[PDB]
Amino acid sequence: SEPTIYLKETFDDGDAWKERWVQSKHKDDYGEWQLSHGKLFADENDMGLKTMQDARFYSLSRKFDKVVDNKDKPLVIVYTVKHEQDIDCGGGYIKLMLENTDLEDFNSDTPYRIMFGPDICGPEKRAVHSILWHDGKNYEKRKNAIAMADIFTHAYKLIIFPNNSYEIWVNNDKEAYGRLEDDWTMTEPGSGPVPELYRYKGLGAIGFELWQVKSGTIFDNILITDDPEYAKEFIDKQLEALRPIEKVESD
Ligand SMILES: [Ca+2]
Image 1 (cartoon, rainbow, N blue to C red):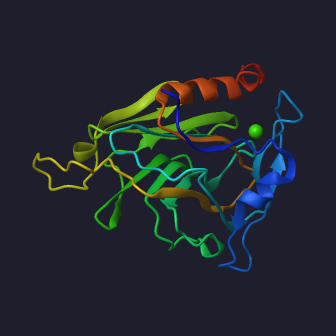
Image 2: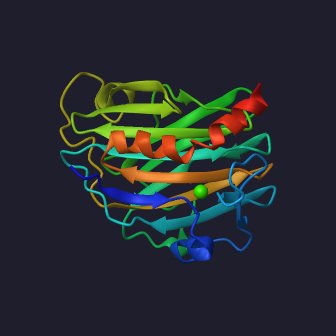
């Protein structure tokens, strides 16, 4: 069928991102954002979203193109993180919220449904957050996927299936998968059905709610869809030029 595109953000239509994304006014000293093609690039016209200030909180959010109801469909969330600055301590994860969230006040205390993406602070903490929602509370995964700490582009992807199962991908490596009821503690420990555990009806906003010490991270290629194959295709095409450029540098 034809893939539903709940959100597609590639920051490539000039200044237009400034009318989609809202800078929260909850704090007066929020970190400041900018478009950039990065140190290593293929096209001096391929831009990502960049943190510009050290030792700051960030809070910038935006509505979906279309509100989500993943009842009886997959839900695919994917985007790219580039810690080109060689990050010491900082978040690189996104927050997914209900559609009627007040973006002008978005912050750490705002309710959210999913928190997903890398979090680095020293060489021990290298975790991919994977926080889901059930019955009024957020729940951390039991064993988080391991995050990338190098200076190159990494695609982080979360897939939720209507049989209450999930996958987590970093690039084309599937780091985690299984059942929602087992790999989290959203449910009572003994086995039993929670039929709509997978369901995120009304999901409609994405936000970067972050702290960074050494800033300079670039986010790009944000897709929220119901089509896992379109998501692999979309990322593969978006990074088609960049991947070899970075591979040359790693070797
Ligand atoms: Ca882009």
